[PDB]
Length: 478
Length: 19
Ligand SMILES: Nc1ncnc2c1ncn2[C@@H]1O[C@H](CSCC[C@H](N)C(=O)O)[C@@H](O)[C@H]1O
Image (cartoon, rainbow over all chains, first blue to last red; front, side, top):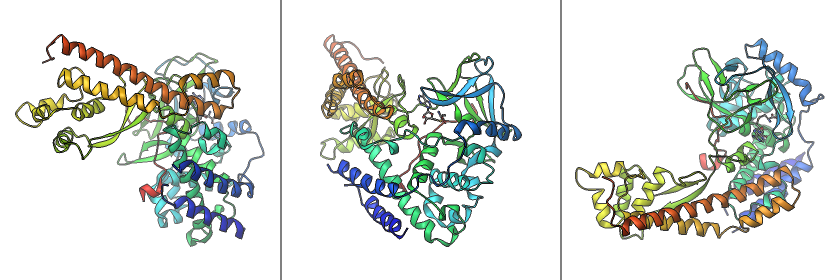
């Protein structure tokens, strides 16, 4: 009791310590503390007597009573994705088959008007971060046995596959990747928030009535933030003025497949509406397309790795150096094109590996002084800036050879900073028997390297292609 | 499409970088 207080205070101090070479050691340090607290607590404060599926009939009845679609599908525990919706009749592509009225959602607005409302006005984090407001909304209603939203809360999972639930050795597979630093931040964010709100809830007057004051475990918080990150959605407010974050019951039981977004908010009728992404025959699982997220984002925020994610990408940080003889001119061209002199870009799995904005950056980054002047002076300078991201209008063959040479060298260098090779990773997946979470970790580190390798090959092809145009003295597109 | 909904949209959980 008083020992949990001292433990969380220690946790708050360490997790508020600034960024520290030593990121893995800090992660293991925080982990050791977190696990010490968790092992001294009783797991989830509120648990339900039934199995998860025993509550799906109540969800359907409650949703039906409040105007949601409840016919044409059923809940099924699928091995690959967990629970999901399965069609009980044939559903045709583009059919409006699912709808959920606003009254059923949990939103920041409904959090503010809940028992959490006093604390929400007083606390700066809750007012500034709707995702965290949503998480505590979820916890308070979970502990309120007569909550309007109990039918939804009693059908949520009780654990997730976000990295907050990984073993240390499962995270260890990600050492030397880009992704591990986002795993580190999420762990430290969540530990710091648990410690801070544990203190707040124990002492703040406006929290005295919260059921969390009786019991608020680390398990509770990890559960609530993972529920929110894997399921939250952005929707308009009632008046269409602003956006807010919302949990959307029933429809959020749909699992993910490749495609286009087919879910939208109907403001005139004040409900979420989902049309069929494809034909679903009776007996087929109903999927939606979650969004164009990277596999790092799917693993870290959504808790799964999606094979054949055509939107996969890795980050690359680039910038014009202040030590560049042409820094001022390059900075001005970038500013006129609306591009910063330094930021993080992406390398994409699909061809081409770079976006128009990264192509524009690389062209400027590789420009001679005469080329830069052509982008700053004269009536055509604005037109040149306009086409700076267009692969069909090169500044010059020479500029292209230089930028593609740079990208090939840089992607190759990045590949050399990984602890394992692509072939070693494929051998591990082939010959080791792994947990779901371990396989997520290894497929993520493999995919980072596969994206880089494709960028090396694409850049090599482009460099050679533009070398030939430069040798054949070919004319530039006008 | 009126107000497309990206399901599980990525949000910022870093209270220190945001406050
Ligand atoms: N294509 C996919 N492959 C594996 N898991 C998936 C998936 N699409 C969705 N999921 C899972 O579903 C979660 C989103 S909520 C969707 C319903 C969920 N399966 C449930 O049982 O409540 C994700 O965090 C992930 O666990």
